[PDB]
Image (tube, coloured by chain):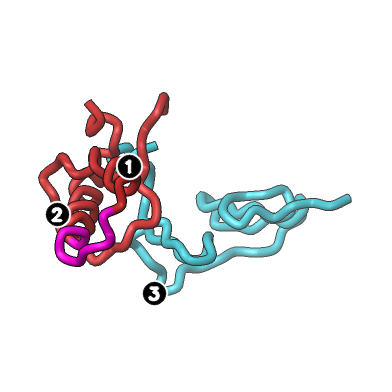
Amino acid sequence: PFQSLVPKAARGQYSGFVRTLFQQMRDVLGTFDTVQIIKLLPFAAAPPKQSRMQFSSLTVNVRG
Amino acid sequence: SGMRILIRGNSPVFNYNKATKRLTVLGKDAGALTEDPDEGTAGVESAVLRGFLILGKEDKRYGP
């Protein structure tokens, strides 16, 4: 359901960015931020793609 | 009176008519414009935003 809101043309590019970032938490210890993980987790569920883009904010569609 | 010139579009102070390819400034006539051979055709417009390229028309895939 959450992925229904995320824009179609960015579900992948977003997800990968989260997934890769999540991996960075498993590699180096001390970066395990509960709030960041909870905030960014729903964007992970997608067929992730790869892009060098370093997002600052992830869009969501709410009532147009 | 402070009139406006729109960065992208036509304004009373500056209206370009493609059909006749003529420029009208404040109602009066300015002349006719030819087309540069280097004139872009992909539709990408670069001088409408500070650091952005207008790649085309609306694309509902990318979101609201």
Query: Which numbered tag is attached to residue A39?
Result: 1
User: Mark 2 touching mark 3, by CB under 8 A?
Assistant: no
Residue A16: x and y in percent read 18, 53
Q: Amino acid at mark 3?
A: Pro
| Chain represented in cyan | B
User: Mark 3 touching mark 1, by CB under 8 A?
Assistant: no
Secondary element type, mark 3: loop
Q: Is residue A33 left or right of residue B13?
A: left
Q: Is residue A26 above or below residue A43?
A: below
Q: Residues within 10 Å of mark 3 (few under 14, many from 20)?
A: few
Q: Colour of chain A?
A: red
For image coordinates 29% across by 31% down, the residue present is A5
Residue B37: x and y in percent read 39, 74
Q: Amino acid at mark 1?
A: Lys
Closer to us: A21 or A13: A21
Secondary element type, mark 2: loop
Is A43 a magenta residue? Answer: no
- Residue at the left extreme, as displayed: A47
For image coordinates 32% across by 48% down, the residue present is A36
Q: Nearer the viewer, mark 2 or mark 3?
A: 2
- Count all numbered tags in the image, as a single digit: 3
Residue picked out by circle 3: B37
Quadrant in the rendering for residue B39: bottom left
Query: What's the chain of the residue with tag 1?
Result: A
Residue A15: x and y in percent read 20, 48
Is A31 a magenta residue? Answer: yes
Please state the extent of the stretch shown in magenta in the rendering: A24-32
Closer to us: A9 or A13: A13
Residue picked out by circle 2: A49
Q: Amino acid at mark 2?
A: Lys
Give the Cα distance between marks 2 and 1: 20 Å
